[PDB]
Image (tube, rainbow, N blue to C red; front, top):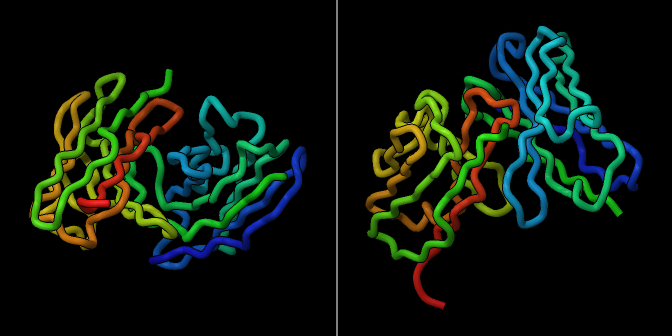
Length: 227
């Protein structure tokens, strides 16, 4: 049910990168494919979505007429091509299953690229707590969001985000009860009770229902107390 991305690139400015995404799990056809990037010491930016309709390309306001989205139904390989590259385009480029109306539950390991309206989501900082404590994480949306389209992701350094909550309060696969989900229009909450050492990562919230940008929050660093 997992997917394999291509190799990392060390391209030059003005030129173009070409990242691939082969899959194996279940009918690549009916399932949507996204490209999300992560700038150095920065948040996650969604670029585009893809089905089998092939005319279901769809890109965010920023990136339009610069990002080319492709997919091959037979060889189950999706692609991402970014033209006129610059210093700010240096990032790890992730491939993930599903975009609009569907939470990103499966992600690729992300290949590195180095160069040399919007529903705004606001999270609550850096937090320092000890194992055993309760963590209350916030999400303020610039406008009201459905409920069906709010999702929480956990990210450890060196690896891809892991879907924790989808549909504001439904736990993803393998997710324990100590992780409890949000509820509202603008005020969303992620509560981590019985805090375990493995729960110390960066936490992201996402808005994946309507608005062409398909946005993520800035991230909350959940740290262990002292130093």
